[PDB]
Amino acid sequence: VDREQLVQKARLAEQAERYDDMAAAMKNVTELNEPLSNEERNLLSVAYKNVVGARRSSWRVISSIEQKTSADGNEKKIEMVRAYREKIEKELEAVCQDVLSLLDNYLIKNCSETQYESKVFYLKMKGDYYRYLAEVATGEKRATVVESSEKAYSEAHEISKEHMQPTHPIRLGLALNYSVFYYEIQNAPEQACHLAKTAFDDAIAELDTLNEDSYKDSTLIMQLLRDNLTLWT
Amino acid sequence: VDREQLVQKARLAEQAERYDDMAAAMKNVTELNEPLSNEERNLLSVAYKNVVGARRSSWRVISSIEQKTSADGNEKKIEMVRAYREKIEKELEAVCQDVLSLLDNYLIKNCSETQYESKVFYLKMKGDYYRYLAEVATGEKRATVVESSEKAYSEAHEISKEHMQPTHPIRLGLALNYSVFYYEIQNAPEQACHLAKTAFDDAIAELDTLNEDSYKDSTLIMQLLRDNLTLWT
Amino acid sequence: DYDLSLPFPVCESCEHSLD
Image 1 (cartoon, rainbow over the protein chains, first blue to last red):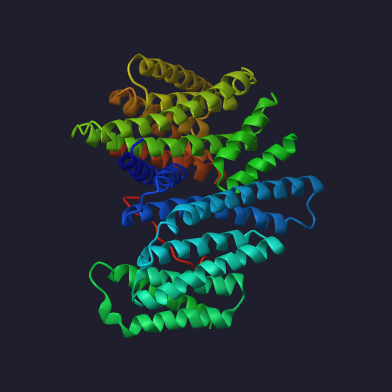
Image 2 (tube, each protein chain N blue to C red):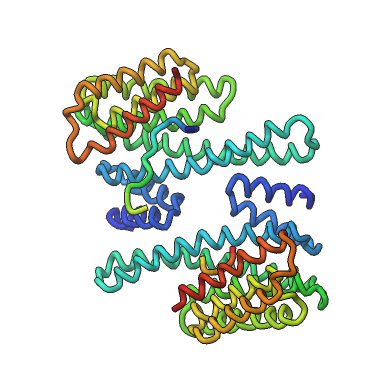
């Protein structure tokens, strides 16, 4: 019931791979209104990434069955498939809204004007989980969560482009997901390519900035930025 | 609500890797009191094995940590681990009692005295989930489920030894889990290895007689019998 | 390469029978 134990339960849940328990424990420590340490901050991101990832993976395979079996299949089986897809859809959207609530009410809110690292970390997460919502949305409900993802990504970009080094893994990771957001959600290959290229180039010019602690995390993201750039011609 | 839809729901949940949903669909198909076909029998077996299997891996990870923490005596971190262990423990035992009820009320009940193949399959399954109970039980509650696992395994063994060919994958796999029960649960290594080699020897004496269909299935379980022998000193 | 976004797998330390 104590905060120090709640973080320990989340550590245990990750070892037991019960990410629903892990995300619930971190949801509690976030609700205590005390700021999150760098480690506790990564426990929350890992927990809800696994939870929303399980729903998103299940949603993708069911929706694929729903589309490829939407021509000839019996009217009774397709009514069972689309019913299962929407059940997963509501589960995904409920987890996303759960994350965006912690972000707007506790995490982004309790950030000072000088906490550019945590501000960019939480703002990128906001654009991430709004992007996950845009994958399963259609019509006017899609165009709004798309612009909410854009407002979260764009603000995280300006704070990162000014107050953080180009080799910082948080700044690099943001440019990755932001450029992915442009290519897959907005269908803007020209802008997605530009965003990923400048972030890679600016990190290359200051390659002599990597320390022994942050050399791994930064270099792999640069490779992923290259990998995504080769794919987009 | 229809049986053909319930089984198709279970196939969806398997592809979506939502084994909790899959076990619930096959529980409904079983609760219609109509005997289960071969395909529906394995859909139920696969679903609950994944459901109870995720709890077995989580319990083993947590109970391993509980052992290294009960020697330090932190008196505060140890109690939170035992709580998480017993939370997973109750989830595991609830899944087992759910399967054992389906076995006693529907599956074994609807087996005629001449349905030797199905009688061995379900009885072995009964000894299996009673053994899963024995892995997390203590005191006299353990010696109870150990005795229940023994009666189910032994009766399935006598039926298979009399009415089944030694190369039959059902009979071979029973000897595997029965020998595993002897070594790991009852700590009777003389009989665990006697059982494993007897079943392996008897199955080779007529291994020439089979088709290729009953060759890959038959031999794979035999390799497991060999692996267990080498790994059991 | 299917999901082109950023993975951060872990933040800690992440049969004998037939199956």
